[PDB]
Image: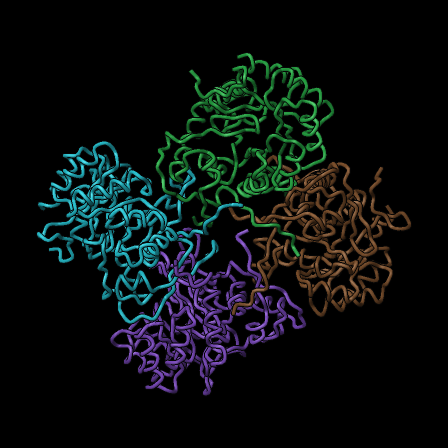
Chain colours: A purple, B cyan, C brown, D green
């Protein structure tokens, strides 16, 4: 009577099958949704990590057609100030903008004592989306905080996470979440897996959440386990609306830290990776190629039509 | 055709699925049972190995809220003397008997002088006798367990090692107050290489747990635990507690004396020096509490019976 | 739910089961077809790669009883001139047309000047035109295959690359005289890492073979072949023949000139591998041994009768 | 339509499950059969390889209670002379014929002079002729087995190598007194790499054992055995005994002479491995331990009663 719910698959267990194709990679549409109310021109979000997203990188992400979530490892007023820098910034045709033409930005909040105050300062600063973001989103604290943000600040979008199950997705949707963020123990050597023994392989987690939210209009953001552009394509076909990147964007020019030379190589103080735009271009190129192979003219087709093969270790 | 009973899974084949949670890691209850009659405040037991448990480490384990099993690689009177040091020795979780003395166990085999060893250990005040061999599903172990229960009814008796439902029932029938689970648990064990014998530990624990459900007989998971994550998995598979061996070897409290070699610290009697036992216990507990937080388990009973696993591939 | 088409197997997932045998390896027949109209005495084709097939290696492949496909990384007139060298050039197995000239093929893409390239190749006497791209299940390739068949009915045309039953039928319906099978066939392929796309080659071959059964259209297995054992497995999975690339690069006949570097021999424009005939002899030896083990007297039996066991990682 | 017959398992895919035990490892019986007519006191046979079995090692194997198969990479008279040395040669388990002489086998192929070789070996007193090729499920091996059985009805004959139920039945039908199982049994073997051919050895043994059940024809597991644990697994899958090759190469008794090279010992014509008896003792110890764990009092019980679990890579 070992209680095994299912066999769960990760990115390396699957490959996308080619299908009949008419639309070239350069001509497919990458338009998607972050939340019920926020559209993005490319399906990429930068993580709320202190080595990844502050105002500078959030601006660059919005300009590329994605969005940045400003991290919460700073004071309330400091975080609000970062949001303000993004909202007040003055050739980028794909730029993610609100109704006033200002760049979009998100900000992360936890569930600790001063969260209510943090949310109010972020909303007053013009934040587009508040991400109620903890290790365990299927919990009383996160569900209640999501509900509170939705009831107190009905004009801001709210994202809840992190989750990995159909049941958690429904609980957050029911609490009023405008999107959910998917990813608990998504990588092989994650702390969560080693220390706690907890996780769900990310391809199955995405598919389980996608099936649970089908017909609700609530997007899901895949957060974790993405190493190559090929994994971005697989995440979308599994049902993600977009994908959150973390350490992949750390060390870029726009990310926090200053450049440092050490033993004939460049680092930030993590290798120095140059302009964010070059990494985004490569990730997009790979997604466009995959859409070319699967014959998917747009994101809606990519999420719903192509098939996987499951493969062995060999 | 080929007689395959089942596919058997080990710790790395599975992960725990998060569930709805209301209780914080710091507030979950870790209380459990070692045996029908012995409660522990944390689910950890130190192994009866000569590099792990003598009086000193057994005292520290009892103080932490677990228990130590004193090894039998010593004379009868020496082993009895080790038990006495524990029984005659602030720590609010301390494992104590009805007289307020620290709890301790002691291992015995099935060889010629076992009866005499058991009598000296019982006279020394031992709380539990572990009838401990490579193969507990055998006439010798089953008979010795029965003998200890009948001769010394005030002492708790643990039988092992086993890996099957049928072995668990035979030991429960013989009067065992708990069973110890682990035969060829883990990849490069001698038992697997030399004899070709073993059962992956997650399946072994689940098979024994299902066999003993409703009997009140605890099962102790012994072997294959490398990280705190494995401790959580062992509990959800059905273990009541977990026995650690080489993980505690090299701690200050373990046998051996500290030795410096090429700028590093070791214990000497090969093993790295690991500092205070309390730091390792704190890490292991932290991990279990985090897992109970993720699965939404408020106590050990919920952790053992409610959460689910997902099975993963090599790529995971 | 997660849209999985199947579990797909590669060469290392399977082994051939021995069967009752009466015919010695040296006596089995290796005769097969490249296309509806072209027979080969051995089931080997050299890839249209610039480090593999120009006139010199194409001549040697034909002489061995196989065929070479001249690469297209050169001007139209240059490629035509390479075909002419082959057509105008003791070898009892030699692959020859009705006029007694050595057979040769030539690759073309789907870009602006393909029509002009095809016409020059056909005028040069090419036996088969390979319409060869990363994604054969596409409007561009299907239309180009149809165009070659309609405009030049007397030349054989091969379409590819494909990995599915549906793609095989689309190319057969467009008039292809054979199809070429292989998309993301190897472990560390760019297609898999960058795009997340591929089908393990044993399953791709079987799926295409089953789709084309009774049509008279051959399939050529292209990719993932490292040892002679893989050649035998490809044939039992349903391939009519197998295309080799980098395995033939560095042979005396392949492009490049020999170069000495740090006490070893290389080719330059890759280890020096000696005469093509020695590699062909090894590959054939292995296929003959496999036919001996399976009891297959000829290629038709090898493709249809023997069985595999599936094996684990261990 | 990929023609997959089954998933096939090797030694590392499985482990033996402990069962109720009453008999100690030192007290279990290891007696088994090589063929319909030849009993052995331990289930071990040395392979017909030129780095493994000539007269010297064959004598040592018989003395241990097993048997050696003398290799055929030598002239007919030379092979006959090796058999004679064994037949004309403190060891209570020794494998002996009715005349009290040590048992020995000898390998033959299917080439031009096989009939003459078999006759010389039989006249030299060989106990069993092993008709031994890469592919036993073939016209040549089946016919040769039948010929040996018809021409020399008083000698035992073994046919191989095979890996399927159907091949086992064809050899049993031809009159084989035992079959030898193993085609592409190891991971990096030539047959797999060059030809793409093989059957993982645990499945091959079980498939052959099921096909021969009730015929009285033994099966010998040949290949893929690296540890004593694999010997136990081979028996529980249905083998009657196990043939060892390179594991015995480099022993004192095996062919070659000892050579010192860079402070280590090798044999020269491979590490030097000391006395054969030490390796046999270790292999037997492991089998006895496994019989202790499974509760099997003898070989018949070990082959028919214990169960496996199947395990993953992580296990």
Give coordinates of residue D45: x percent, y percent: 53, 27
Residue that lies at the very extreme toward the front in this rendered image: D214
The part of the image, by quadrant, that contains residue B144 is top left
Up the image or down, C50 lies above or below A269; here it is above
Q: Nearer the viewer, residue A235 or C56?
A: A235
Q: Residue at x 26, y 65 (%)?
A: B25
* Quarter occupied by residue D280: top left
Taking depth in this image into account, of B207 and B12 the one nearest to the observer is B207
Q: In the rendered view, would you say C277 is above or below C12?
A: above
> Is residue A91 among what the camera can see?
no
x and y percentages locating residue A145 in the rendered image: 32, 78
Left or right: residue B140 compared with residue C111: left
The location of residue B38, given as percent across then percent down, is 19, 53
Residue D158 lies left or right of residue B270; in this view the side is: right
**Quick one: C70 or C206, which is closer to the camera?**
C206
Quarter in which the N terminus of chain A is drawn: bottom left
């Amino acid at each position: 009577m070992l209680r095994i719910s299912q066999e769960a698959l990760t990115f390396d267990d699957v490959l996308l099958i080619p299908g009949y194709s008419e639309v070239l990679p350069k001509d497919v549409s990458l338009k998607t949704r972050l939340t019920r109310g926020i559209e993005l021109n490319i399906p990429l979000v930068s993580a709320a990590m202190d080595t990844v997203t502050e105002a500078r990188l959030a601006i660059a992400m919005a300009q590329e057609g994605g969005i940045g979530i400003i991290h919460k490892n700073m004071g309330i007023e400091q975080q609000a100030a970062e949001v303000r820098k993004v909202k007040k910034h003055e050739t980028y045709p794909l730029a993610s903008k609100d109704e006033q033409g200002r760049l979009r930005v998100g900000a992360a909040v936890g569930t600790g004592a001063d969260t209510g105050e943090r949310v109010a300062a972020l909303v007053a600063a013009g934040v587009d989306v508040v991400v109620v973001d903890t290790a365990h989103g299927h919990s009383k604290g996160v569900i209640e905080r999501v509900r509170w943000v939705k009831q107190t600040f009905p004009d801001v979008q709210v994202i809840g996470g992190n989750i990995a199950t159909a049941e958690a997705a429904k609980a957050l949707a029911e609490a009023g979440a405008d999107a959910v963020k998917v990813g608990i123990g998504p990588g092989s050597i994650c702390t969560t897996r080693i220390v706690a023994g907890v996780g769900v392989p990310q391809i199955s987690a995405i598919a389980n959440v996608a099936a649970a939210l089908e017909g609700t209009g609530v997007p899901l953001i895949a957060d974790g386990g993405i190493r190559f552009s090929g994994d971005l394509a697989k995440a979308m076909v599994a049902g993600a609306y977009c994908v959150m990147m973390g350490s992949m964007f750390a060390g870029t020019e726009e990310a926090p830290g200053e450049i440092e030379l050490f033993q004939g190589r460049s680092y930030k103080s993590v290798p120095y990776k140059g302009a964010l735009s070059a990494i985004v271009h490569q990730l997009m190129g790979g997604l466009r190629a995959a859409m070319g192979y699967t014959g998917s003219a747009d994101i809606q087709q990519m999420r719903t039509q192509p098939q996987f093969v499951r493969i062995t270790g060999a």
